[PDB]
Length: 419
Ligand SMILES: Nc1ncnc2c1ncn2[C@@H]1O[C@H](COP(=O)(O)NP(=O)(O)O)[C@@H](O)[C@H]1O
Ligand SMILES: [Ca+2]
Image 1: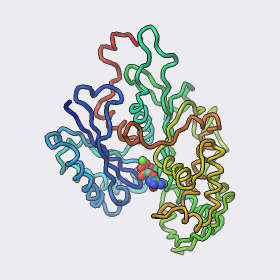
Image 2: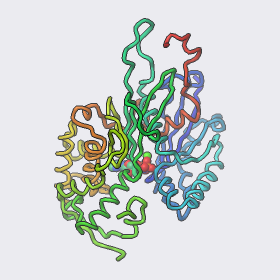
Image 3: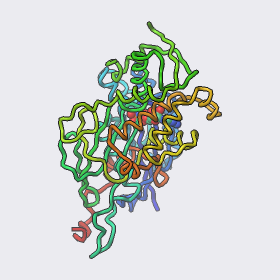
Image 4: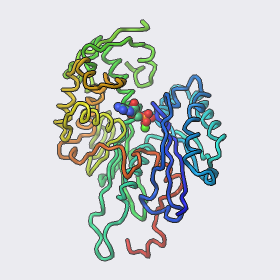
């Protein structure tokens, strides 16, 4: 079977990853057929971290692009499409400096056009794209778009689809199929996939990614407490104020100050709860910050930093997280650890360790008070980062859309048998 290939660079706020996908030439339109062939993690920061030195943005991709030449067979280089899609890191930079944004985009374009792949552009995704393409990825890999049954006996209602929650470094997305009336066009999505219509809700909360939330909690802690109740007792660091306050997410809230943790789970909870404005809703129902959201429903996969954080809680802390009440207890126990106690659980490298308490607490509030999961809906949420040997994220769904590999309708409308 002759294989075709495709490459997406996911240029996220904190890192770039390259994914290489392969599929058989003559089965390319079947759902669930495309899979991941390989991947590469670019060393250092995301492309937006090179705003003041844009040529390094392109250079940073070279090691992974060299790997792609070895991963994809040589006779196939020229007809392999390559895409770069950039997310909230580049969206935040476009707020600060559209000129610096264009120069970063020009530097990666210039590097990518030097390679023999069919280079199809470097683009910034909208938040909607980001959310919807992650939802397409998860459901395509799990074959949720197959029409189940057979003639004279189709399953009814049709197979449910998996909602997607993506916790990135600078934004977070929530996307799910819904039968609720749409009250905000900015959230409303209609897809036509394999002959079927899917009514989907999506929203992207810019500045509610993990790294921007950790910055906002640091600015907040500095302002209200002059200690960090989410960091563990005995941990301290020298905080550079210009770094804290340069983000568009924190400029809302001495060059160096010392800041220490206090392991105070209750003050940590109070600090995180200030992130969610629930006072005002111009719609019949909101998530938070005045944003329209219909009731969460169906199964969900929570990936990226949702997965990594819960995996810390289950695997390193040894704590169960099957209910919202367990996840909340796991958070308190984590936040109550001292720095020596936390460090004694992690024999190897400790980067991110002081932050798990804050992120876990944000995730618990995001789900229960942001999105209004309760014990009943939360039971339908799985934390996973892979499906069918393929990393879950927006890259695959992006590549599928741009390469036109999901047909709106089946061939001949399958003789109309699905009508
Ligand atoms: N091992 C880990 N433990 C906890 N968090 C981890 C992790 N590995 C990556 N992450 C976090 O996932 C997030 C991935 O986000 P990105 O794709 O870089 N940000 P965006 O442009 O999608 O908004 C980062 O915050 C990263 O630090
Ligand atoms: Ca991301």
